[PDB]
Image 1 (cartoon, helix red, strand yellow):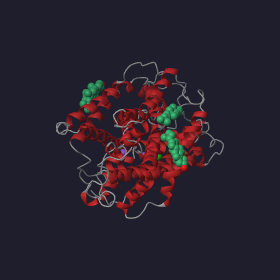
Image 2 (cartoon, helix red, strand yellow):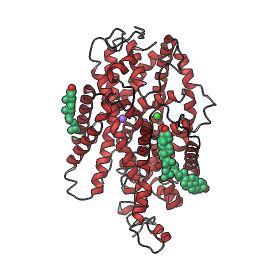
Image 3 (cartoon, protein in one colour):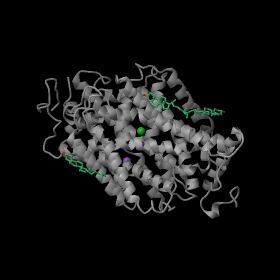
Image 4 (cartoon, helix red, strand yellow):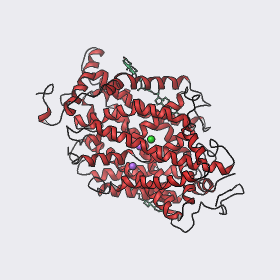
Length: 542
Ligand SMILES: CC(C)CCC[C@@H](C)[C@H]1CC[C@H]2[C@@H]3CC=C4C[C@@H](O)CC[C@]4(C)[C@H]3CC[C@]12C
Ligand SMILES: CC(C)CCC[C@@H](C)[C@H]1CC[C@H]2[C@@H]3CC=C4C[C@@H](O)CC[C@]4(C)[C@H]3CC[C@]12C
Ligand SMILES: CC(C)CCC[C@@H](C)[C@H]1CC[C@H]2[C@@H]3CC=C4C[C@@H](O)CC[C@]4(C)[C@H]3CC[C@]12C
Ligand SMILES: [Cl-]
Ligand code: NA
Ligand code: NA
């Protein structure tokens, strides 16, 4: 297969893939729309009781068999729909991740001047409601009336924004060239691309605290509200954010772990990566809410009403902070360069996983010698599918894709995989498999979370989400009926991959009765187990 080589290389490559735009762009606006401090307690509970155990499960699953997201299912051939749904979710995410990266590119290209274009209120696109520190904010007017030229409805396509299309093309070309010339795999300066963001965030942090009114923003960020805790909407949002930030059902974790050595310690790696990834979102939230408190202090409004609940909270808040620093364009350039690097690090692995999965699935040697053409085709398809998101109605489609297609399918897929491993294969067998590599049995906390706690929590969240479903409540953006139907279809497309592949496999399995056919399709194959011959001892002996 090809081992990773050095262990520190794996730890640094996993941190660079886990930390991305979901830490600095997605977390703050979800936290703001979920009433700030009322979102933190479910978030921490979810992280402690569902995220880390499933992260460890995925890493161990990848390491033990030395297979990717589709080859690990020799343990139960009837559950390949899990990997197929993982691939579907990865495609959905990667379609619009590059659109966000291209918006970041556009903001980076506009910082190469002497005076920032979002710093004053006298521009041709400004109105009489403009109000600036040297009502409405100049940054939000720049975001709405100039960068996007937003429409009034999701069904009003309007025209295509040419600069955004150019930025998208540049981003896709950069990704393709870096992938086919091997920038990260056989490359360095992953240390710098892991150290730079914290320096930038620390620089932005000191200025925010000094501001007037930031204390109220911080208090709103930290103070918990106990009234909104009895609602299934906030818990589902917290679970979605936790599973999205760690990449649980993306399929890249298994592929990355497939190159690890047998006796590598995946428990320590999982703990370290989870803590590092989740400690980065809190810093960005601190900075963002300090900026929000300062902004609400001088606009004569409350912290909960200063901004709207759209996805463009970062592109309105961060430029306002960047304005107040001495020599603003340099800091803006550095900040947006850091954002671009954070996005590209995740996009590289996202596309590499799909290409590797396709190449391994096809299986011949002719598809192995034409990997560059496969990568080119995938890149061209992604670029073509991302074009309708650069119109005047693109942010509506992006929001629909974000909070319908890649929110709660990850949790369902992860729970199904955990249940299949624990109750169809047997928990004792998996515990012995883990002890084979680590040398000690998994701690009791992970065992109890794998057998009882996490599946029950996910079941309760899913059950109470449906019962408490209100059309007025679960819309939040006044979308029409057909848009909601499209979002539901996108949500169901990845989940329905499991039951349909189950029937497909059952239609080709020998056995008189259906019960007999259900036992042959769930039995492990003949090649399940350790890859190397020296580790095939005990219950795997020939
Ligand atoms: C092959 C895949 C991976 C990348 C796609 C390459 C092509 C289609 C891309 C790369 C650079 C892009 C161009 C960059 C700049 C501009 C200027 C803008 O005013 C019109 C669009 C235009 C002309 C873009 C159109 C599409 C473009 C030519
Ligand atoms: C049991 C398995 C086989 C099927 C489960 C499918 C159902 C129950 C699940 C899968 C994904 C879930 C959806 C994912 C995302 C959203 C967006 C949210 O804004 C409204 C709820 C909604 C729409 C969820 C409702 C329930 C849902 C549709
Ligand atoms: C993936 C989700 C959203 C779809 C529904 C599947 C889950 C929630 C269901 C299907 C099988 C169920 C599990 C089957 C067996 C047991 C053993 C029991 O001692 C504790 C509950 C537990 C663990 C059940 C809890 C809920 C469960 C995990
Ligand atoms: Cl996060
Ligand atoms: Na990244
Ligand atoms: Na993350």
